[PDB]
Length: 205
Image (tube, rainbow, N blue to C red; front, side, top):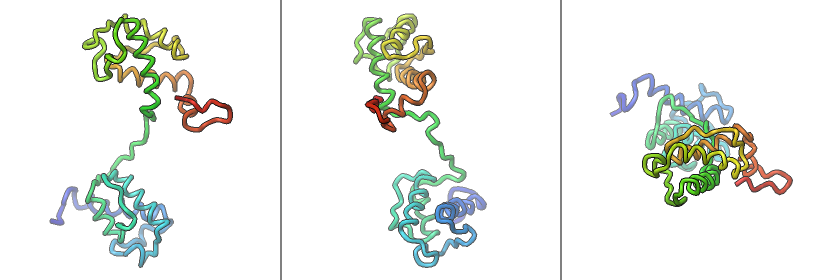
């Protein structure tokens, strides 16, 4: 019906506010001058250049499945209708990249890390699966993996001074090496492949 479809009464009205706020903050319009039945194009007089950032932010803020198309955003209530058509959460948390990592970045760490453990322990690199537990499935002993870390950092031009807390999964330690980069060598490592610096040091992967 239209009586507490998902959230309580106040919460559902604050839902209006949550979407209203997006229309206001991006354009410079007062959210208190935004009326739910106001057709954006006509009454508020918002055009595509501004409207598009709103549709964009609405899709991102509430973390919708499908991106709202700017031709499909007609009126505020109409947008609200569209919001809930995919996904909506009151008091949604915009979780940023707290870890801030890319699978391409940890990948090259992951290549060498497996090679050393493999060579050291007498196993095959490609047989060393990330979903497979190192000690349990892969059959590598704690000493076998821990001792190999040192020479691994050496082969990786990283501080062998630092140790990897032995994680039983290759996925975990791969993330650990990726963290070592930030903690030992700075965020600079990823910055190279992100923002290409003047000298030929663009290859940060």
